[PDB]
Image 1 (tube, rainbow, N blue to C red):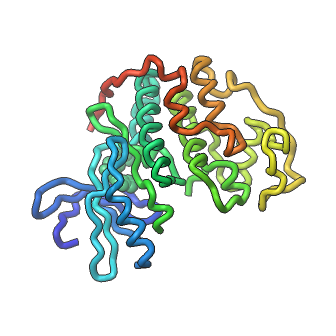
Image 2: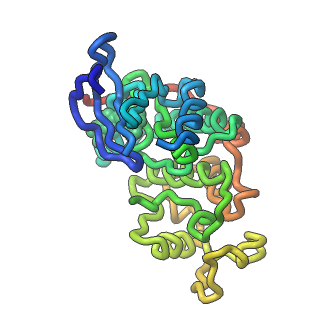
Image 3: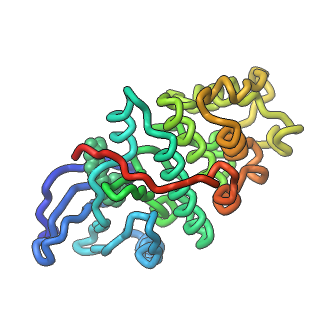
Length: 280
Ligand SMILES: CNS(=O)(=O)Cc1ccc(N/N=C2\C(=O)Nc3ccc4ncsc4c32)cc1
């Protein structure tokens, strides 16, 4: 805490405040996260600094002093949310959307292989740089240690042991948002969130989701809505994209496409790595 010079507040998070800081020694610019200390957390966090991948924000150091916990991460200048706002008028070029989705899936496939979930993906957690790369931030902090727009159905229905599938659902929601320039399910409460999903994808039943009527928060009194055509939901997206999106938004967590299989989807046959025009 004394070895860093806080430059600016980057924003309050779920587990703490994040600051852009300069290492008073090395002189390097980093992202300092003050966690708002259980031994289990220390161990779980420790395993994360060994998780290195080009599409994951690197956890540089863990400072545990005076019974306080600070996480030092690599620093990137902008998040996807800010980039989307800046591109609201023209929208993000399809090639860039494809590139970003492709890299995010590589990052998830890597984390999922090590059995590490995110559980709380959102545009604010996706960081981009001038090189055309995009990285996932906050990976694993949920295990070691409010927007509901990207929350998977199983979580909303009370399933306690969710899987890697919840991250695929969130990514599918972000995918749709980049394409249409509007959040797909902008709920303002848990029941509103659930109902917005049902009104679009249809109220789930035992046919599409075996075991759904046995979920802890499922109510037989839920209204029964019909499923809408994806052509209406994400209009400009081509057939390959709609096909991939539909598999990312399958109700049944077991039928939902995995990150690895998504990487082989036809939608990515012509993927490239364009460079975005960022205004820092
Ligand atoms: C509000 N968007 S903006 O682009 O205008 C300002 C801005 C500038 C940089 C960043 N980067 N933030 C982060 C960064 O560089 N590394 C991180 C590691 C963990 C984490 N947990 C939550 S954020 C966050 C970051 C995020 C916001």
